Image (cartoon, rainbow, N blue to C red):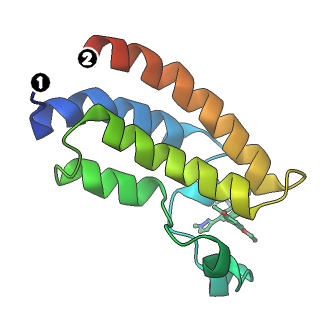
Amino acid sequence: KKIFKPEELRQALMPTLEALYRQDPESLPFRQPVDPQLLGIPDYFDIVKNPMDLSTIKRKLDTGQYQEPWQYVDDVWLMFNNAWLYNRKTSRVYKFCSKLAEVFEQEIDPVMQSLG
Ligand SMILES: CCOc1ccc(C(C)=O)cc1NC(=O)c1cc(NC(=O)c2ccc(CN3CCN(C)CC3)o2)cc(-c2ccn(C)n2)c1
């Protein structure tokens, strides 16, 4: 029954999202929604039914869509899980995803401990 105001969540969590944006080159596939037609992967939405990317998560943070820290974390991991699902383990995007997940863990673990 602990209440998290949107400003407090945003202040605590936005640095962890910024760390993902900063990661170069590995965030490049993740900074915008997947465009299946433009990227040449027209079957994408046949596999990924709940797309998620950094810019969608940022907008939800900026508009107070997350009431709890774990709701933000779940969207970050939805982005990772989509990329590990759609892309082969031998592929650029799967490998970039794996790196982003390691970066996110380093950032989010201390923020969680201090948020409760
Ligand atoms: C083909 C299939 O793709 C995909 C399949 C599946 C997925 C998902 C999420 O399941 C995602 C994708 N997406 C990508 O793989 C992708 C990859 C890049 N760039 C790189 O990986 C990269 C490494 C080094 C350089 C050189 N770079 C640097 C910057 N410099 C201005 C230019 C040269 O680029 C970029 C983009 C992208 C989309 C919009 N934008 C503005 N950028 C998308």
Q: Is residue 102 above or below residue 88?
A: above
The quarter of the displayed image where residue 93 is located? bottom right
First in sequence: mark 1 or mark 2?
1
The residues tagged by marks 1 and 2 sit, at their Cα atoms, a distance apart of 8 Å
User: In the orientation shown, which residue stands out farthest toward the front?
Assistant: 1
Looking at the picture, how far across and down is residue 35, in whole percent? Answer: 58, 78
State the residue position of label 2.
116
- Going 35% across and 42% down the picture, which residue do you hit? 72
Looking at the picture, how far across and down is residue 58, in whole percent? Answer: 34, 51
- Judge left or right: residue 108 versus residue 49: left
The amino acid sitting under disc 1 is Lys
Where's ligand 1: which quadrant? bottom right
- Judge left or right: residue 98 versus residue 23: right
Contact between marks 1 and 2 (CB within 8 A): the answer is yes
- Going 37% across and 53% down the picture, which residue do you hit? 57
Q: Is residue 58 above or below residue 10?
A: below
User: Ligand 1 within 8 A of label 1's CB?
Assistant: no
- Going 43% across and 43% down the picture, which residue do you hit? 74
Q: Which mark is residue 2?
A: 1
Looking at the picture, how far across and down is residue 90, in whole percent? Answer: 90, 52
**Which of 70/37 is in front?**
70
Q: How many marks?
A: 2
- Going 25% across and 17% down the picture, which residue do you hit? 116
Q: Secondary structure at mark 2?
A: loop
- Judge left or right: residue 48 versus residue 87: left
The amino acid sitting under disc 2 is Gly
Q: Quadrant of the N terminus?
A: top left
